[PDB]
Amino acid sequence: YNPSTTNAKDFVDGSPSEFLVDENIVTMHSPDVEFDDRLQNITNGKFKL
Amino acid sequence: ITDGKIADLFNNAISQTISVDQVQDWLTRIADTDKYGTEPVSMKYKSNP
Amino acid sequence: LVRIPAQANSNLGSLNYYANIDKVLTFNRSEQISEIYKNGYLIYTTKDW
């Protein structure tokens, strides 16, 4: 949106039930998580991708 | 709700609010039973030790 | 609920994530995107029988 014209709220109110994709936040799916229950309890694990 | 802006109108409830009877356009279009509330309120809640 | 920690070099906060969604999506009607949406979302059918 152009901030000089409209606010964020007024812009979203034209279609508040619209969805956008997000590749900046992804969802990794490995068999270890589903089958190894030790990886379903990770909490803020410092890892590199 | 003028243009779909229901978020801004929700935000500015302190200003954009008035009773039904005081709406000068609705002095004869609304029945006396559809502008005054005359039913109880059910107060029910529990607490902890 | 899974609060993704804050992402570096971004003034945003710690993001909030859900994968079990129980939502009802409502179309608020307005002319911001196009005029014809003051009545609702259109119904799409075949050109002929």
Image (spheres, coloured by chain):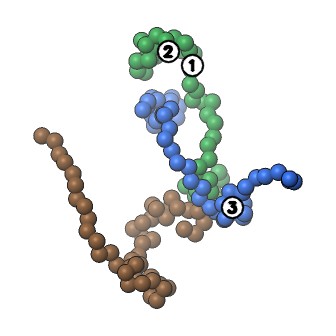
Residue A7 coordinates in the image, percent (x, y):
57, 56
The amino acid pointed to by label 2 is Val
Query: In this orientation, which residue lies closer to the viewer: B3 or B14?
Result: B3
Q: Colour of chain B?
A: brown
**What chain letter is assigned to the residue under label 3?**
C
The residue labelled by disc 3 is: C37
Residue C1 coordinates in the image, percent (x, y):
42, 32
The amino acid pointed to by label 1 is His
**What chain letter is assigned to the residue under label 1?**
A
**Which residue appears farthest toward the left when viewing the image?**
B49
Alpha carbons under labels 2 and 3: distance apart: 45 Å
Secondary structure type for disc 1: loop
Residue B23 coordinates in the image, percent (x, y):
45, 82
Query: In this orientation, which residue lies closer to the viewer: B18 or C29?
Result: C29
Camera sees residue B45: yes
Q: Would you say the residues marked 2 and 1 are in contact, meaning their CB atoms lie under 8 Å apart?
A: yes
| Disc 3 crowd, CA 10 A, few/some/many (<14, 14-19, 20+) | some
Q: Quadrant of residue C3?
A: top left
- Which residue appears at 62% of the width and 53% of the height? A15
Secondary structure type for disc 3: helix
The residue labelled by disc 1 is: A29
The amino acid pointed to by label 3 is Tyr
Alpha carbons under labels 3 and 1: distance apart: 39 Å
Q: Colour of chain A?
A: green
Query: In this orientation, which residue lies closer to the viewer: B21 or C9?
Result: B21
